[PDB]
Image (cartoon, rainbow, N blue to C red; front, side, top):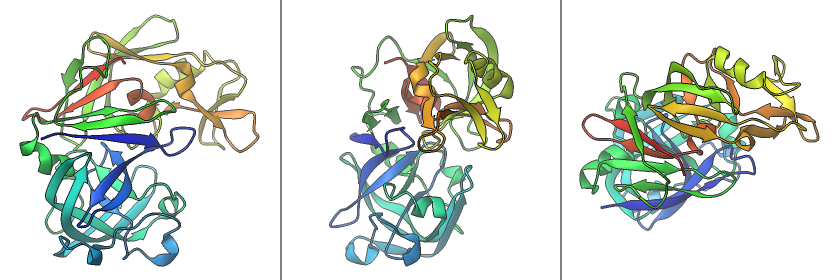
Length: 330
């Protein structure tokens, strides 16, 4: 089997991408944030505290003839941005782009943190990291991809995120028309539960490539590119007037600037992020200070190849017995 679904930016900055997901019988379609940095499929629901729902579409398990309470199971998750959610668990039929999994754990939110409530466009998350990170207790549950894997034509999914445009998540096949050149594959460590890999270096604009190992994670659920402070300083030094602002929370730059590109290495290959992808717009409405899309990971504990980096590539998440990642230009 295969599946193919369009993923759509939630706003004009590409802050996140939503993908329609069919849950239950008859189908209830929710727009979920596919997140290769986490491993829970959770949704706003008829059980979510009413004051914490503000415009999201909810899953109502009592209206699904295939929903079953997973007795005794609870979940609770906290994300790198400080947000969180928790609740109970149902199993139900879940379909993405024509690919159907029966008995998928659907984590129904009883509580969500304010950042979720305040974002009416995201109805939940669909985790695509390794199932060892799934938070369901006392019996950890598998991700949608893990449940689908054996049925897929090939045990892979691909992320093709658009810049200011829709893109595609495919399951079970590699669309050879969706990229240019060849796909360069690179080793993955699953020791932390992430799609963790080592970039071979970077370049700023037309500058020389610096060969240096940068361990990080491929994370579709993180907006920005978070890299070591040395790398980030080297980038922003090429933008006149750019500076790190403690009050704003990262590097800002004059909105009148033209940003240089940023290149990262994948083996001997190179992925170029155009400068425009690094502009996240005014820090507040009407400001001439703009927020940068490359930020320091120093306070995170891990480097994160988020959407800024991934949307410059066609990315293969190869879930074979020994997983690997593939990157192609597009």
